Length: 115
Length: 118
Length: 114
Length: 116
Ligand SMILES: N[C@@H](Cc1cc(I)c(Oc2ccc(O)c(I)c2)c(I)c1)C(=O)O
Ligand SMILES: N[C@@H](Cc1cc(I)c(Oc2ccc(O)c(I)c2)c(I)c1)C(=O)O
Image (cartoon, rainbow over all chains, first blue to last red):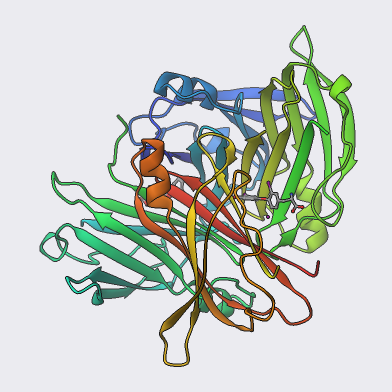
């Protein structure tokens, strides 16, 4: 239900080996960690979470972009890239978090398949 | 396919369906020759746009009718058209995906030239 | 004004007016302490957000209430908020401009470090 | 000035200086006539690019030499050029700012229209 696609805007390839964590907002305004992962070479993570693990609610996906640029040899601006959103996965609703990275800029977009 | 597209609608949060596009190749005299046209499907893609044989190295211009897209959406767009012009280097089984993120008053054109990082 | 913002609305093609934001500084224990808040004017900027005195070297978080902005505009947006987290090195009159481009289902955060 | 530009370099986190550009106006026959050329300064802008008298309503094309910008940076660019094509409606003292966000394999073209 939750997929990601991270692209490197400098190299024109997906951003591989990007560490991420998915958190779910709790009733008291806190966060609970529901999964972690690292993108494969296609800048994707497969079987990140399952349907039952992704009920309606506010989610935060944190991407370790600083480590990504460091490893690539660039010094980046952001300490992390955070994507915080409301998810309504009722039906067939699948979410793709598209992330476009440059050392001093990123774009976070979502593609939400209907039901 | 050596040339793929992926168009996203940044307003609706879905791929941009029914976007008309055309692919032209720069000729020796500096003019443009149209080699393919098409319209994106519901996934914001166009399958079998051109073949490897139709894609020798050279300068290509892919023009997207984003103005009609927004107009059909009931929106007011800025750009007359979205243009992506690039020198293609297909040697070594390099394929291109032209990613395009659309908003009425903004678009982002990115290119992916491998399916994997390195 | 070591810390400036410039927010644009990619749907309307104008700056994003009345966008609420808050600036937090990371503390020794890893937590966040809020040092300023503001709301963008019609040019999508906030003047005199913080002073050089308030902006020492360290890690900062600028959080923009984009959800409220889109809700007010009449759209249902994706993001609950827009978060910009960065290590600042303002020592030496280093200015930071956080440029933010907004659409209901996408935003771009860029930095111009002068 | 009815037509401004603001070019940023997303790799360095600075405006993009010394970017060459050309402004053309579409003619009645579908062709193009050049009305201005310029090069951005260190703030990624070009001052006094054209006058209001030179900017009537119509379709304009602004071509940015981003390929040379990246080549000079020692990088490898994707795009052969960056072109921004739009129907301009300056009536009622509307000015345009073409914002351009550059990375080697990606750029964002946005427009800001203000009543100034
Ligand atoms: N196999 C599918 C996977 C796929 C999914 C999506 I959403 C894509 O678009 C992106 C992704 C990240 C970005 O930052 C931007 I801008 C656009 C691409 I490119 C590929 C396909 O090829 O469409
Ligand atoms: N802030 C001053 C000048 C100014 C105008 C604009 I539009 C700006 O935004 C940009 C520029 C390029 C980009 O690629 C992106 I995304 C945003 C900035 I930063 C500054 C003013 O307008 O008075």
